[PDB]
Length: 281
View 1 (cartoon, rainbow, N blue to C red):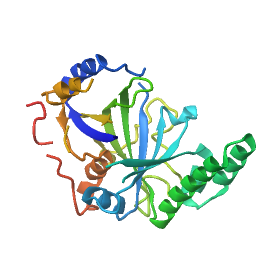
View 2 (cartoon, one colour):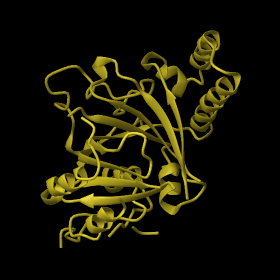
View 3 (cartoon, rainbow, N blue to C red):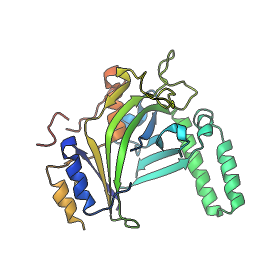
View 4 (spheres, rainbow, N blue to C red):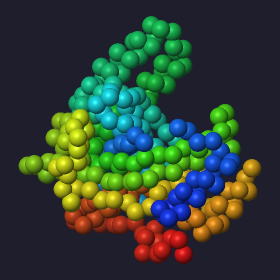
């Protein structure tokens, strides 16, 4: 309450797993989700998240669909305190560079000003202000920058107004480098919050992606957030089944860093989840 459990699901079992969940939870009803994770060039956040030091926050920009359609963009900081705490800010696209590269305070200022004018309670205005400051200071203090993106499609299962259980399955998971590490020819321009090729509004925006710039993850990732390892019993039948493979402490952030940069001599440590196994057997 609330506990998170993560599983890998083989493509061969994906449809059966979905049909089983659907018997107990309605499904929300194609667009890619983009999650663009931050770290510094020493991979400190990755190191902490894997060793489990310093509350091990992760930080990402998240938006759905094609950046062209002007989606909402979230900047989200997640920290495990038995319970994950999430600080989530909605950022207007054109302020992102200033906010993450230049310590700009003006988007916060304008936002609070508007909300205050329209009648948001003081206690709320103040909480929002703390959220802005905590995320920006986190970025500045630790020299965080956008490093890599995960892209995937999500199927989400959830009974309205019911907290007990909630289930997501993410498929088509791909990791893509988006760092400004190289002083010449950085993948992402150092003053631009995202690499601009893959977000271009064109037929194939992945045209210029190089092999060493992406990695595919082979399984779907199912997360069950509950109020198996650490009404309720379809859950047991499912998760004690050959159909899902529970993976204690799985982190998509850690996996993406390892998959992309492990062969590039940036990392001292790698996760060992125990992907040589056939997860079906």
